[PDB]
Image 1 (cartoon, rainbow, N blue to C red):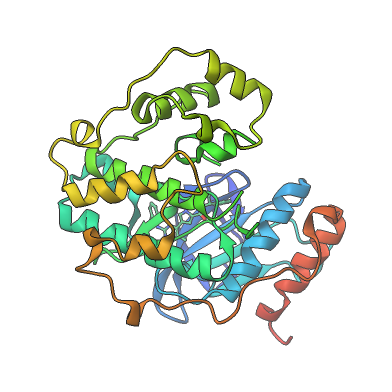
Image 2: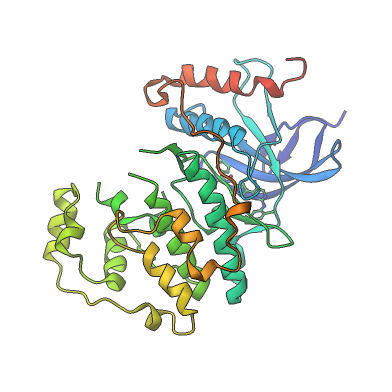
Length: 335
Ligand SMILES: Cc1cnc(Nc2ccccc2Cl)nc1-c1c[nH]c(C(=O)N[C@H](CO)c2ccccc2)c1
């Protein structure tokens, strides 16, 4: 017998079906590896999570599992298999088996210059997947380059649905609403930040802290209008913003001198301060910049909207642990 697998001192008890592990990434309460599947004869991605000590991690874990099990779309990552201990007393870790992708957008932007057509094509696939997510009445809430996975043929899939929620983060990609004390339009903002980063290979709003984040935003958009501020904003944020000196709006064509003016027009409509005036996903797909890829015939939507039977916030982590145990039962031999 081989014994339990191990990656960087950390156990990976992924049975005899999954072997040849390599580190490919990490998260807050887990680690991602690639592995050889001896059944399907492919290498896969295994996501190990260890959520049980924290009630929030348990919540995210259950939420990600229920959603990815339900969603079925080519621009969304799925779950092919889930491994965990045969008993609830023994369950300290959950392993989620997923299609292996070549890399993420974070890394690609780190060493590659994108042509306009590739920007255009990546943008299309993000929005297409976001169409499905939003049709399901779900917010991803953490769109960013490292959560966008790419394969050898530039196919794109959204990953990490841990922060995903039923319709009502990373600082650089979070909408001004979020920080001003939300709806589907927070994802559009993130997609905007991502477009801007594909254009110049650098984040458009790299705030060191939440305050510095709001500065960077206003550093391009200009001082907020009266109506822009009026949104049940917290006293702190509003007073500070009102105390700042005037900031002039920087034109997109000056910040991205060589960018397709169509790309910039859409970029403008996504990075709109006021979320009510921000472009929605379908209107985005239909934008002239994407005409070459827009195909309403081939852009599927969720059969029905998503809903949670129980209110997960209210549940103690021991109740949540039980639910993760049950949700993952169907992947258990016998069953
Ligand atoms: C699911 C998946 C499939 N393939 C790859 N490939 C890949 C991506 C980037 C660099 C190199 C490679 Cl080979 N990656 C993934 C993947 C990437 N991130 C995650 C993921 O879900 N991460 C979250 C945090 O973002 C996480 C991970 C562990 C524990 C909690 C949360 C899966």
